[PDB]
Image: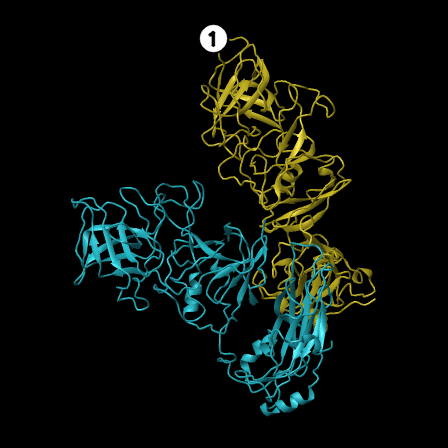
Chain colours: A yellow, B cyan
Amino acid sequence: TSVVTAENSSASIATAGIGGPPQQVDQQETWRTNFYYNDVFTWSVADAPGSILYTVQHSPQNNPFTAVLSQMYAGWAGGMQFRFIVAGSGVFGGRLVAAVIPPGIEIGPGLEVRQFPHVVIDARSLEPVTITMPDLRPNMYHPTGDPGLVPTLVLSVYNNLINPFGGSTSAIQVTVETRPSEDFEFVMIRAPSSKTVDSISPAGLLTTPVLTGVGNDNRWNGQIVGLQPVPGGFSTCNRHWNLNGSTYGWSSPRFADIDHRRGSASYPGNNATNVLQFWYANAGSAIDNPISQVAPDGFPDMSFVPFNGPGIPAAGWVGFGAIWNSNSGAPNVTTVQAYELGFATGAPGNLQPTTNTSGSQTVAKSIYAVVTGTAQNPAGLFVMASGVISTPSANAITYTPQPDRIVTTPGTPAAAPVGKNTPIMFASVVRRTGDVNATAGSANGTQYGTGSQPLPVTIGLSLNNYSSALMPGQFFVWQLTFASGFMEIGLSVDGYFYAGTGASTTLIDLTELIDVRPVGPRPSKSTLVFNLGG
Amino acid sequence: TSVVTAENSSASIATAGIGGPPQQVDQQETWRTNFYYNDVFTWSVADAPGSILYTVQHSPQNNPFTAVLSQMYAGWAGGMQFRFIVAGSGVFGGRLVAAVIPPGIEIGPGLEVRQFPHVVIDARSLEPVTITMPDLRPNMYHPTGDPGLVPTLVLSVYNNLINPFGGSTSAIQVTVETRPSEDFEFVMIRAPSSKTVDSISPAGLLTTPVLTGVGNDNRWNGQIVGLQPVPGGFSTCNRHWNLNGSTYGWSSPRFADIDHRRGSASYPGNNATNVLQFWYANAGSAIDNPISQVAPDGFPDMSFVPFNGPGIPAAGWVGFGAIWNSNSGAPNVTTVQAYELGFATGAPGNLQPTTNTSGSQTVAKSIYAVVTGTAQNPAGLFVMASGVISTPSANAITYTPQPDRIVTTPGTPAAAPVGKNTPIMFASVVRRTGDVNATAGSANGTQYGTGSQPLPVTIGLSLNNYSSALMPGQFFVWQLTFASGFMEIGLSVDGYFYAGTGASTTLIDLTELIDVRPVGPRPSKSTLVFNLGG
């Protein structure tokens, strides 16, 4: 075998002797002789000449085996060899340029990689193309924890990609591989406790059994069976956490309980027998909720539908609950019922649905008859957190909610389709009131309820800060593999999830889904693949 | 590594010793061992066999690093190595021939490159094809400033390019790369003050922040947000500067002021209360303007629309201004109003719009009521240079101007679509009179006003002479790179800008535009690319 050493090799082990004798310097060790996978990027026909497709800074992490060895060593020095395995086709054309940009030069649109010392990679190349990144460093070694100035490896489009067919295929995958060079070394062994870049990548929170096993939504605690796209956009802010340590809304991530103490109660009719109890409060009276004052913790963020009489309302959010008096509260025995909660205006007269939370008032009307009706001014509610959907007859209404019924607070980031990508929404089979036995079989299509993001993701995002873990303008992409196809699923800086379905409103079933796999950050201009089983 | 020396190598350093010892002659210097980018040309399927695609004369400039080193050296001698990296495809066919034509032979259509000593370059070649241009010179060295007779490198079509598909892709990009040969040298070090070809290429005047940042039009001082093509052609001559140091029109490039002293004034009606003041002068009475006598400096070159009564006219050019008496002028206090200016015939009776400036008369009619109306024969105007567009109601009329309303002087060069290319026109969002709050958001589409060329280009072209900087029959091409595509934009010998959209009238938005890049001269038969985001 032949392992290529760097140009600055003899002065690299010489000046890194301030760390003592070099460690893991044995050239017959396999982890130093073989190339191993590092990354995959995508080269589309929409890429301009001169545009940068791949960028990596010099670091052991670029190799899977020097990233393992760097957690026991407090320092490194030496180069790294990169290989480029274009998937390609013999009908595609266009070249790439790869050059090692020295420290002190910007990496941006104005950079002319073609006038650096470079290597050229064809779109139809069989053998992989190799370049060596030396360790052109001003520090004498890079301590793992603050490495210093490093060279950068930049792939740029030389000639733009052409496909002389037309549609269908428009992007080529290029696989980066990585081997240490002959003068790479480690110094100053440390305890494996912890160190290195002191941040967490957003990769391990979304694993395999989150979609084909356990895993729940943000609205009901239902098992995820589908992703359904929406074209045009939607907004959710209840249990939706963005990539920083913040949210815009109430409802801490737990389906426990809804409890409110102060608010008015009423019932219609002159007779206090077999009526519908109606409870109301304004927005901003929730003193007990430490996150947001606009609602009690666990209140559903849907718009109230105006219904009257004995008719069961279509769609909506009902939950089992009771009303309790204040002053060391013991609830009334003769009122426990299913209640539909929501947001209205003009209570208790002409009730209209509301879109914005400001200027709205929370309402709670019973759907079934109750033999007693109270009207005391201090009163509250106690409603379980998990809910069901009220329906007039069986059949199947629609997936609930629609994108227009979902209430938003002021200052909320909205999902927008960028390119051919479109946002998705996670579906779950939920029980209903028109048919309790809604097993997923025959007797009409079962009801689907859709939340924004998976809860495991909400729990694992709430604690950690990811302000630099994903570079804005891109999304982190996972690779779902079914039994007869595969798909790419993205995750932006706002917590939204993307798939490149385009203008389609068809539910995608995770029945035959097997495994997922991290890839990394990838820009929003690249279309996520849709090679499904169909 | 191996660097190939020339055939006339031993007699090249020998006869260039009249300059003394050779400089930058060190073969281990990287700038002499690596190939670097020089140019890109395009090989279309419309190219005949024998037709010349690429031509370069022998010069250090052909290399990015000997062009840097030539500004400190007053002389050079030796060869240069060229490489040809065809982007290609495995489905394309056809060959090229590259030969070094000696001095004293013409470079034209009758030249048979295939019977010179040549190299053959396939359309589907993976490895680059190398040729060496020796320094076959009659002078003993080439002083930078007057080099003398040089050999020329000519690429010609051997077999014409075939695509056995049909449409879509019809052109291949070929990338020229360049390395100095072993006997290249510099002599007689000079001060870096300045020298070399003593002219400026038209490349640095159109840079990145001219389109996604600062940058204004020739009609209003509005920020450029779009390019819109027109099929059929248009003519503009007001602040439109061609590639020489000349123009055909008035209005020096500055939005300062419009001031005219002599000309007649009138108002209709027997009552001198709440009338529309109307001022007129003939074409050719502007003594104060040193460029052209046909107009005052800053007068808008649009055709007057005939309107009467209290109706606000559709389209047009209005500006805020007042009338002033002569003989050490102090203006009248009781007449300051918005005025619509323009060109008419048959004033003050039957007013008709005019196309040609000869035989026309400049008119200036108020659109709003004014409590005093003068009729003195010596009177003038003072109108601000920046203008707005008068509109009856809100909505959106059209982009203004249309190609037919624009007045031309006699002797004006007209834009014509050549091939599939078509001319473009730079758009800007301008304020209107029907809606002052024309922020680019909701409440109908905002009004777009279109000028001919960017002002930075007018300022940077006015001073310098470019009579040989662009070879006629071609255009200089820049490479715009968006977030999801790219485009080629040309610039001819007449100041017009071209894009290869074809027969389309759709506005192209520079919202996602990032960077531009110079390429060079490219002929008019080559279609500029349109790989946009759609």
Up the image or down, A213 lies above or below B403; here it is: above
The location of residue A212, given as percent across then percent down, is 74, 36
Residue B477 seen in the current view: yes
Number of marks in the image?
Answer: 1
Q: Which residue does the numbered mark 1 point to in the structure image?
A: A270
Residue situated in front as seen by the camera: B172 or B232: B232
The residue lying furthest to the bottom in this view is B18
Quadrant where the C terminus of chain A sits is: top right
Per the image, label 1 sits on a secondary structure element best described as loop
Quarter of the rendering containing residue B414: bottom left
Residue situated in front as seen by the camera: A93 or A456: A93
Instruction: Identify which amino acid the numbered label 1 is placed on.
Output: Asn
Please state if B375 lies on the left or on the right of B288 as rendered: left
The location of residue A340, given as percent across then percent down, is 56, 21
Quarter of the rendering containing residue A127: bottom right
Up the image or down, B262 lies above or below A288; here it is: below
The crowd level at tag 1 (other Cα within 10 Å; few <14, some 14-19, many 20+) is: few
Quadrant where the N terminus of chain A sits is: bottom right
Residue A78 seen in the current view: no
Q: Mark 1, chain letter?
A: A
Up the image or down, B398 lies above or below B530; here it is: above
**Which residue is at a point 63% across and 71% down the rendered structure image?**
B52
The location of residue A171, given as percent across then percent down, is 68, 52
The location of residue B65, given as percent across then percent down, is 60, 75
